Length: 131
Ligand SMILES: *C(=O)CCCCCCCCCCCCC
Image 1 (cartoon, rainbow, N blue to C red):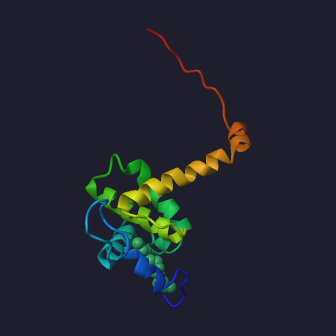
Image 2: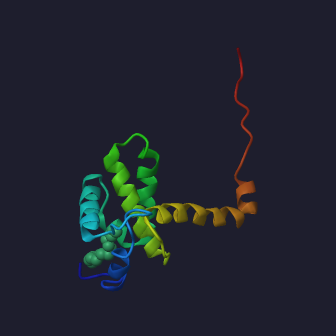
Image 3: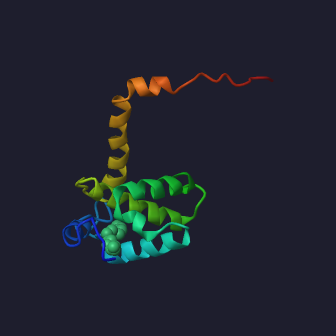
């Protein structure tokens, strides 16, 4: 709309800079965004959530636990939305895969810097074990 806060020109260059495959020659294009923004509108998810890295976290996290149940359609969104996330956090990816992996290894840092926080929230639940 008339109120943006992402880039509008800069990020665009980077977007088309990311490759669709690890060893391919294909790259990302508007077709992917527009398509994603639309689909989201149907999944009760505003297309504006992809505007801020924070928003994506909510989207990806939702389709995350669904990447198994959902069809190939849900897998297409996650892949895309996942990439943009890296760009929004100022992360230079090499390919669609590099993005997904980054989002993972990245979060790993938090765990290392939360040895006290994690210990505070945790318990040992001993389930049953009969014959
Ligand atoms: C009007 O105020 C909003 C128009 C500008 C928003 C575009 C920035 C976010 C790009 C959409 C998601 C990209 C998916 C890779």
